[PDB]
Every structure is written in C-alpha cells, then in structure tokens.
Length: 352
Image (cartoon, one colour):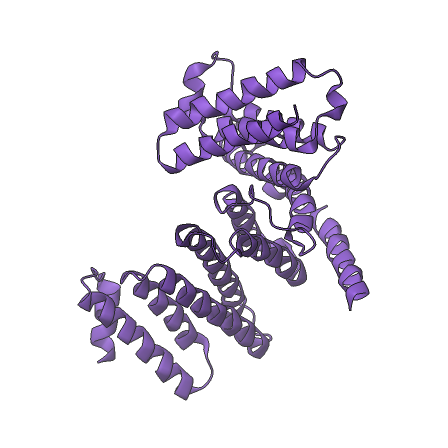
C-alpha cells in the first residue's frame, strides 16, 4: 500500500548503498539561464555562453548585495550551479573568455560545490536536487575519461572512482522521480541529458550490480524522462527527445537480459521472458515515437527490435510473425527511400 511504497522505496535505498559502496531577482537569474538554453537549442553557442557568464555575474552580484546570504533560497544556488555546469558543458567555447588556468572539470567541481551550498538554504529543493544530480553525473563522465587517460589513475578500478558520485546522483534523482514531486519547469528533456551517463554506466558496469538495483535505478531514470514531458501540451519536439531516451533505456535493458542469455545456461525461460518484455516495451515506445515523428528511417529501428524478438522467442509461430514484421518494416523504409545497408538488404532477400 502507501506505507509499503515507503517500505520498499526504503529497501531500494538500502540495497542501493550496499550496492554502490528582490527575490524576483532569483526568478530572473533562472530566466537568464533558461534563455542560455534557448540559444544552445538554436545552436548559437556563443550567445549561450554570454547568457551563462551573464547568469554567473548576476549571481555574484546578488550575493554581494544580500545582507544575509543564508537567506538566499535553494533556487538561487540551483541556478548558479546550473550556470557553472553549463560553462563546463560549453567549455570549448567558454574557455576562450577565461585565464589559461581553468578546466572543464573545475567548473563541474564548482557546480557541485555551489549546489551543495544550497543544501542549507530555505525554499523548495527540486531545482537544487536536479542541479546536484546533473553535476554529479558530469563528474562521473569526466572521471571515466580521466581513468582512461591519466596515468595516475590507470590502476584504480573505474567503479571504485565513480560509485560515490553515482550514489550521490541517485540520492537526488530518486526523490525527483517520486509522484510527490510535482512537475517543475527546469525539468526539461534537455536538463536530463546527463541521465545518459548514468544509463551507460549501469549498462557498461552492470555486471557488478544486482538485477534489482538495475530495475530500481532504471525505473527512476524512465520515470524522470517521462515526467519531463507528461504535460500533454509539451511540444512534440520535446516529447520526442524524452521518448527516444526511454526507448534507449528499454532496448539497453533488453540487451542486458539477452547478454545473460548468450552466456549462462540458467534460467533461459526467465531470461527470455524478461528480455521479451523489455523488447515489447521498446515496440510500444517506438510506436509512441513514430506517432510523434513519422519518419521512414525509424522503421529500421522497429525492424531491429523485431529481429531481436525473433531471435529469442521460443515458439515458431511468434518467431515467424516477428521476422515478417521486420521484413515489412525494412521494405516499407526502402519503399520510402531509406538507404538499406547490406545487412537489411540481405535480410529482405534471405527472407523472401
């Protein structure tokens, strides 16, 4: 029940740890950051950088003109943190405006430090939790890169390096994913891009996590992507970005079960059903995507999903259906002028 939602939710957090181990000026800070994201979306990244540094300078100015900085709301630290992270994100251009002793990673560290400073402030915490999560996740990505490229780190296991920030990210994502956290406009598909770092980390090093941990953390991710666009009046364009991430997450999870299949001999039945289930969640989401953006090359993706179903299903009747659906999707794509790679071409020939 409702008390069970908290009893199980609590078990998720437990296994998770074990597994991983005036004022109106605030609204206007956010506006500057939001506008920087509008420019980024329009691919004018120089302007996006200007708006970002503008946000930071305005944050500094609010701070020095505030009698008591401990009264600045969480949303102030959240906006400032988000601006700092955006400098890291756009660092290739942003570095041009800075002294040479500056790094992308240092801006990620600052974004983390600034959001953490908000943990103490008054006010709604949603935007802060999102800022914290986004910054922790960019830190993960950079640590992965440092692990592959810095000689000092070569012999430290990636997971050892990175799990503490993965754990912190999940600590702040989990509450945002709850239905008790009402939607809020900083929760955009754009803002959730760092969720890809978490997904692939889990995928790439899933071999060290329980199944239950994966299912727990993956449903957090899915829940967030979906929430960023549940308002039925979200423009299709944004719905698209979220649904493609959800689809990536479903196919990734299917592939994880299919991987266990292609090794271990137990329990094929269990593994086949779970894999199929995610593959079918994929078809559903793909269909949702296809209504949002009917584009013939997408049919090749449907075909891939159906071939995976064909590959693992245990009854011939279903297998024949899947293969036929794949074939039909591939032919229609081609009939709509989509270039078929030799793979696909040969599958249509091999089939009929």
